[PDB]
Image (cartoon, rainbow over all chains, first blue to last red; front, side, top):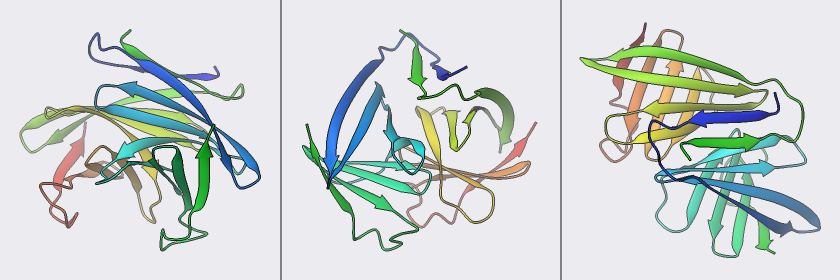
Length: 97
Length: 97
């Protein structure tokens, strides 16, 4: 296969945005998938490839996928692994590129 | 468009399972998208159509999407809306069909 096709119950428009973030000394390729309310972000992490959904948040866009939290405020974003850091308070900082 | 294509960085196999759950007196069509670690569930809710990702859990499969929590233990599953119920403790019970 190689690809996940989610068929949406409508003719909604679907957009794909890719961003390069630099997290410390590592690269991270994140691709966003937007279709109205639906918003996914595929995190191509070294540890495991994750597809996270946009979850409830107050400021920024919080994304939840496997054990990961991808929280983006603008060009900045915080990477949380909930097993490395169950408190969700010692994130890895990333910069958009 | 009408469809979300997530292109996976590999030739992993991708499977699609659809289930009918009955939640009280309503129907719910849920489709699961599995590709290794990656696991999504499109919830075709009356309120809004949601695509949730599999998140960290201890028992069952917990899925997070928008303000929704879809938690499945077997044929049973609990639907939480975090704005209706911020405590995540008064779920709507659903039965597989």
